[PDB]
Image (spheres, coloured by chain):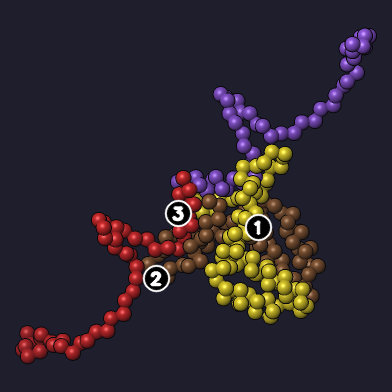
Chain colours: A yellow, B brown, C red, D purple
Amino acid sequence: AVTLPSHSTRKLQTRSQTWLESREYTKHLIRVENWIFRNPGFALAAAAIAWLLGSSTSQKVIYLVMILLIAPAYS
Amino acid sequence: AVTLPSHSTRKLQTRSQTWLESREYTKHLIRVENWIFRNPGFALAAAAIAWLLGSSTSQKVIYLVMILLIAPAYS
Amino acid sequence: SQEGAVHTALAGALEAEMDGAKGRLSSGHLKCRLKMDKLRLKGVSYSLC
Amino acid sequence: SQEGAVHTALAGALEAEMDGAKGRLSSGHLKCRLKMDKLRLKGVSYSLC
């Protein structure tokens, strides 16, 4: 079907490498990087929505990052 | 491969139904709901990491929701 | 076989059917202006039944 | 088919092999205490060569 829950949630930990280990890092990094490289306008809109939220600067930057990570996965 | 960019980003719009229309809503909701139901403790961890951040109450609840979405996708 | 992954990746794309070399799309739209300057009326000048 | 999905859905699952009705796992973890009080030294009482 469509959902198919990922198994890296319950990663079995042992000295031997797991089934597809060499790919996780670039997996998530590449998905986000590609999605952003396609649509920059949303980077602008996310900057604005972050700036209008949050009092201090730290909260604003954290909001920027969390929006930029939520939108690519549509999670 | 592992990444496989989703096409709903570029949802082709017209009167006729698209390839898999009936599945999008429950797709995303089901993924999130199942992941949270499997691991309850992260609800508490997210509540704490929210409460430590953000002055107002509304900002803290927005933080809680955004964390509880960004985690199930490991986005 | 990587095929179901492509099938669910193709979420939100239009279907289409194909016969022979030609493929007939299933959804689109067009913009046609209708020059109705040479439409007449067949009925006028007929007596009532 | 959706198999290509199950191959990527599995990430962080151990690989195992199978012979007959038995399955050999090659990645594990065992805890054993070693009673080494019935070991002797074979070399004792040997002239230096």
Task: Name the residue at 80% across, 30% down.
Answer: D31
Q: Nearer the viewer, mark 1 or mark 2?
A: 1
Above or below residue B40? Residue A16 is: above
Task: Name the residue at 48% across, 67% down.
Answer: B10
Q: Which residue is mark 1?
A: B74
Crowd tier of the residue under label 1, counting other residues whose Cα lies within 10 Å: few below 14, some 14–19, many 20 or above: few
- The residue lying toward the viewer, choosing from A4 and C1, is C1
Q: Are marks 1 and 3 on the same chain?
A: no
Crowd tier of the residue under label 2, counting other residues whose Cα lies within 10 Å: few below 14, some 14–19, many 20 or above: few
The kind of residue on which mark 2 rests is Thr
**Decide: marks 3, 2 in contact (CB < 8 A)?**
no
Residue C7's disc number: 3
On the picture, is A47 further left or further right than B28? right
The x and y percentages for residue B58 are 73, 74
Above or below residue B27? Residue D2 is: above
Q: Are marks 1 and 2 on the same chain?
A: yes
- Mark 1: which secondary structure? loop
Q: Are marks 3 and 2 on the same chain?
A: no
Q: Earlier in the sequence, mark 1 or mark 2?
A: 2
Q: CA distance from mark 3 to mark 2?
A: 20 Å
Residue B14's disc number: 2
- Mark 3: which secondary structure? helix
Q: CA distance from mark 1 to mark 2?
A: 33 Å
